[PDB]
Length: 213
View 1: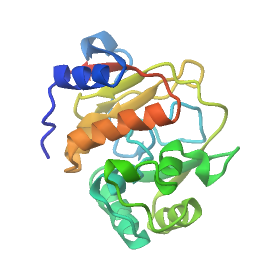
View 2: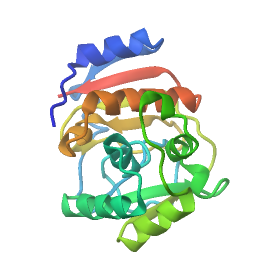
View 3: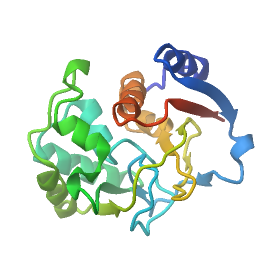
């Protein structure tokens, strides 16, 4: 699908939402960015450390839940199809939880399952966090589990195709691979605004750096 928003438009929309936002170049982050590895899990934007051992995969809110959420897919069967679709498209599908809250450890899914997106026009999932994880695992996905408290300092919205930024548990940041929404045919403006709202509702930092190629 089309990314449709220009970097300046993304910065402007976020500023209108009360965010501090700026554009940074792929060049400025040359040493930090990494090419996407097909063996890496498509995982959450969560900036915490975890038990992940499958690195360099794309980052989307809630892992593959970002895809179901944007598409309005709310059944376990639909979740299973998305799990298989992601796997068939060059990434190992994943969703995650944490040690303190188990499967409600994913902030994005907690917001979704409890209706925090109702007013933005999203249908609610017809399953709970445990059921979703079981379905993703059954369909061949990975269930990642984080540890520690959220300490993200900034949000990177990466528009550089087939590259990503990795978590740093001691110098955390939310990483949103906007280009991946395009890859999966998502409505990109809805996806980006949902990502911004997610950070807002979870009390994350309303500070963004849009990475351009």
